[PDB]
Amino acid sequence: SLLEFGKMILEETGKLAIPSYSSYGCYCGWGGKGTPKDATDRCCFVHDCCYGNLPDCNPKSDRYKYKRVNGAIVCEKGTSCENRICECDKAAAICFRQNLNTYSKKYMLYPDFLCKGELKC
Image (cartoon, rainbow, N blue to C red; front, side):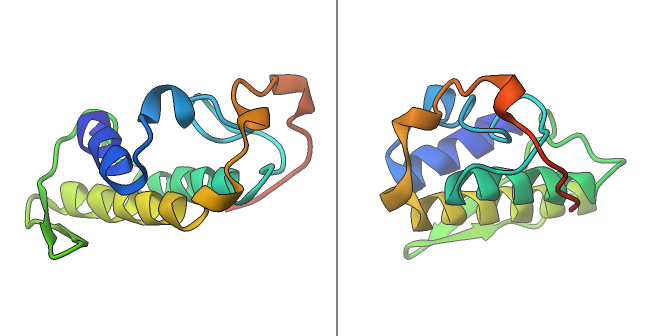
């Protein structure tokens, strides 16, 4: 769920999911269209794709459990949906952490009409 995902992001990056990552670029947050603007936006794109692989899971509302084994995020055993949601979210958090250096405030609240292009998952 968004509860788990938001927490993961904050632990990982030190930034609050809302509003650092809820309206960044073309893909972070509501919907997705166009070509991702940067590395961070590509993480959101890949994350949307990941969820897109689970048409009968409910990633926003279904809660899973995870723990940290030393630094590392480890998804705990739940239903099959919970496990796969968790792996999607975990990958996004790490991707965010890996691209914190190129994160750009210029892309916060990015206007929709500038999200142009086709990108398939």
